[PDB]
Image: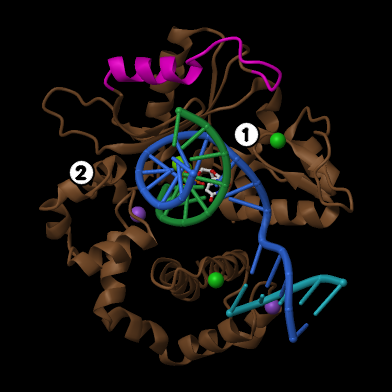
Chain colours: A brown, B blue, C green, D cyan
Amino acid sequence: TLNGGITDMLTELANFEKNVSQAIHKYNAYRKAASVIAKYPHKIKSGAEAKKLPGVGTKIAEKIDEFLATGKLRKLEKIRQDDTSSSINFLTRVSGIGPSAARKFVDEGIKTLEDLRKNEDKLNHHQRIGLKYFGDFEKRIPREEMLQMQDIVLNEVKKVDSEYIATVCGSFRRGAESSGDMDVLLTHPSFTSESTKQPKLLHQVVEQLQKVHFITDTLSKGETKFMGVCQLPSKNDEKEYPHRRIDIRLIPKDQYYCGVLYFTGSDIFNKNMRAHALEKGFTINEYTIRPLGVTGVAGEPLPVDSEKDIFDYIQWKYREPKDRSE
DNA sequence: CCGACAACGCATCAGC
DNA sequence: GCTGATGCGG
DNA sequence: GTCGG
Ligand SMILES: O=c1ccn([C@H]2C[C@H](O)[C@@H](COP(=O)(O)NP(=O)(O)OP(=O)(O)O)O2)c(=O)[nH]1
Ligand SMILES: [Cl-]
Ligand SMILES: [Cl-]
Ligand SMILES: [Mg+2]
Ligand SMILES: [Mg+2]
Ligand code: NA
Ligand code: NA
């Protein structure tokens, strides 16, 4: 955070282009700059110095100089004052509400937490739960609580079927001291890229996590991706732990490494590694990495037996989870 | 210049 | 009912 | 908004 001031500015600029401008690319460009500048081991003294880092162009360069001079960005000072932009930005903070639904509500005149509350009949299921746990979801999860949640999830899963393998990924696997949520990659021998010999593999687990009252709500649930809520149990007289977001992804066992790579992130690391991958002539997703013929069509899945194998194909020196926090 | 920008599961809608 | 486009995730 | 060709 040697440049915490600069990277926050870019993030705010990025959330704006995304929520208000619905200009996803500017959003991604800004996040990239914030990212590269964030790992830069020096306290940036000027736009020029920043323009050197890849991802930082001329526009961002000027903003950084202005920011270093005045201590703020005019363009942001204005954005903060515009009521429409502040409403949209706010609503989007509710899980389930994005740029579109956010702008839609404002038109209707629904632009404050009070409004959403007295208009629950105008939200889909996810949005409703996102409203219910509005505060909680804004709270980070201390690694210790993560470790505690991990035990429940792994033990409960072990109970449903000893052959289930549950690995906690996301920022937890990258070793963060706090996480925005808990991410769980789940595999079982019956579900392989070749065949699904057992149905409801994800359902059963979710069902077990519910019986023990660990999982309390469901944002969305399909055969391989579950999006919901959970809560650590509290002791007698102890004030309750906040409700936490939980993501569970069922992946074919033979595709574990591509799956764990992806789910370990970060999102920006994935974006960059996948981008590079293409440049090297490959395509990478949560399931496999494949080659690319001039035509464009992906080829057949290359053999993978470790995360490193994936790094090797693209000719990138392996990077432990802790170093993928971009 | 200017196209490209990672990738995909689920919820929900339009159109048939 | 389906298929496809869009939103959201994030 | 930035980038490589
Ligand atoms: O846009 C995305 C989002 C997530 N992911 C992957 C990487 C990320 O680490 C993982 C889990 O998603 P989260 O949104 O939970 N992010 P993460 O766990 O890294 O951080 P946080 O602590 O905020 O949850 O899914 C992507 O590839 N693209
Ligand atoms: Cl854009
Ligand atoms: Cl695939
Ligand atoms: Mg996470
Ligand atoms: Mg998550
Ligand atoms: Na640059
Ligand atoms: Na939101």
Q: Is residue A277 left or right of residue A238?
A: right
Q: Secondary structure at mark 1?
A: helix
Residue A288 visible: yes
Q: Establish whether labels 2 and 1 are both on one chain.
A: yes
Q: Which residue is mark 1?
A: A260
The percent position of residue A257, horizontal first and vertical second, equals 69, 31
Q: Is disc 1 surrounded by few (<14), some (14 to 19) or many (20+) residues within 10 Å?
A: many
Question: Label 1 near label 2: C-beta < 8 Å?
Answer: no
Dot label at residue A142: none
Instruction: Please tell me which residue lies in front, A145 or A186.
Output: A186
Q: Is residue C1 left or right of residue B1?
A: left
Instruction: Indicate the amino acid at tag 2.
Output: Lys
Q: Is residue A63 above or below residue A205?
A: below
The percent position of residue A230, horizontal first and vertical second, equals 31, 31
Subunit bearing disc 2: A
- Quarter residue A126 falls in: top left
Instruction: Indicate the amino acid at tag 1.
Output: Val
Q: Give the mark, 2 or 1, whose residue is nearer the N terminus.
A: 2
Which quarter of the frame holds ligand 2? bottom right
Q: Is residue A294 above or below residue A143?
A: below
Subunit bearing disc 1: A
- Quarter residue A182 falls in: top left
Please give the range of residues in magenta: A192-213
For discs 2 and 1, the disc positioned in front in the rendered view: 2
Q: Is residue A222 left or right of residue A90?
A: right
The percent position of residue A233, horizontal first and vertical second, equals 25, 25
Instruction: Please tell me which residue lies in front, A235 or A276.
Output: A276
Q: Is residue A100 magenta?
A: no
Dot label at residue A132: 2
Q: Secondary structure at mark 2?
A: helix
